[PDB]
Length: 131
Length: 131
Ligand SMILES: [Cl-]
Ligand SMILES: [Cl-]
Image 1 (cartoon, rainbow over the protein chains, first blue to last red):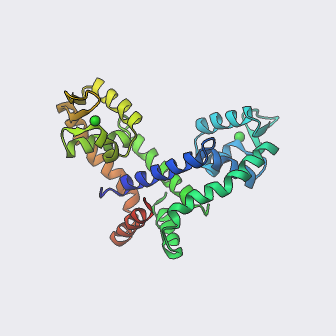
Image 2: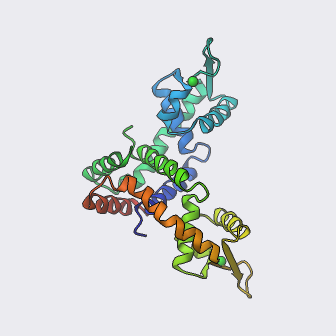
Image 3: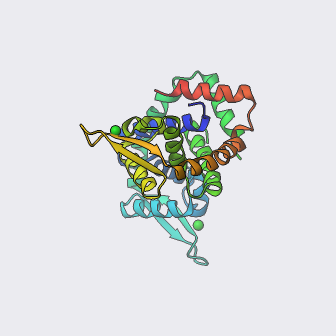
């Protein structure tokens, strides 16, 4: 189709289909949340919304599941228990460390079809299009 | 972030957030399904999966809801009732006709930030990346 955002969703679906086959227990939003916590241990939960590309409700559901699976621990602001700080557990570090080369490989199946200049330009257009 | 597919999901989330504000009762996958039925009235349901970018389960759920809202009608293969043909109803035509300029406008908020050459190239890279 000639609609750029339709073809973009089609590319996204192919990338998601490969991701779910290679990492059946870690979606891309879950993976991004773990990468963002690892990049800033103790990050505020609210700041983790933008860092991982999520929403308040979706992140809350996601962190509850990771917490129940021993992958994430959280602490609270004593002045405001609605504020929370997030760390990866040791098990969460192992899960993320094993997933990174897999996620990189899935990304590479698509980005590797582009030259370095094409990859840089693709990124530039996406940022140019964003608000 | 330097990950192209992370920034791409961020662009997708912004585009989805605008879409849901302007068309609160018609998501992009629902809109694409209606556009594909209108482009080929009587299209086989199975062929509508690729045309609208969906899955068998998701399309089945989606067409059931549209059918229950008087937006879609379906007919069956007499030899194999699992095969189905899909049409828009008159109400479905009106819903789609009203939605098209809205969806175009939402697309334009992002694509309009690119020149015609940048838009053509963005599309070319996406197709180059797809399988
Ligand atoms: Cl917080
Ligand atoms: Cl069918």
